[PDB]
Amino acid sequence: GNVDLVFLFDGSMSLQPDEFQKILDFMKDVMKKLSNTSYQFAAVQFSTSYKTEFDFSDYVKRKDPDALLKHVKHMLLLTNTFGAINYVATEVFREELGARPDATKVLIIITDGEATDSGNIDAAKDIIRYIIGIGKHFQTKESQETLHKFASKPASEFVCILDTFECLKDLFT
Ligand SMILES: [Mn+2]
Image 1 (cartoon, rainbow, N blue to C red):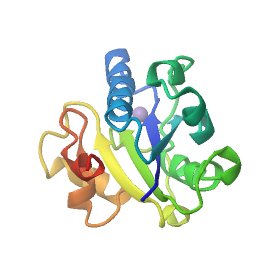
Image 2: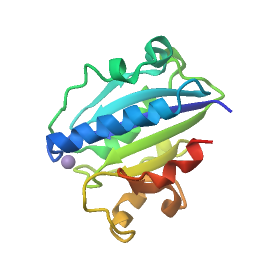
Image 3: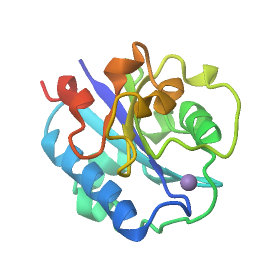
Image 4: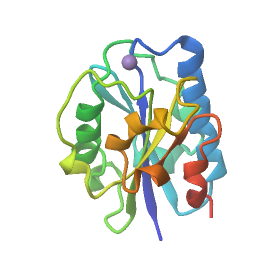
């Protein structure tokens, strides 16, 4: 089965340079691990606003993770995670941008959990949401509870940390 996976990465001011760099590295690693498969990728940076760094069509055209994230500039503003999730649900998974109608829609959200906005993400209900916690404050399962609201259910199976990203194991099959 085909899969359209979007990386939604936190680019807020709370991210230290080394941490933001770790996020970019993680995205590159995930893409190289799923190269030449039925997976197609898109990447969206979010802080106060939302920016599609590359879409599905760009991936098909260029393929190279290094060249795809080359123009990325750390936003360094707020953390509007809910607005970001909504932006992806309506502005990214579009046929005009290379999205396949039949493909399973997957979202890999990379953030430290703290959102500066609120609201509902019903427009993203049909998207499978995996949440990858950044930083050294998600060492325990209890601390990961703060990420539950953004993930698909059961939350315990769609939430993990940047270091190991064990919750993504099924994607690599
Ligand atoms: Mn932040």
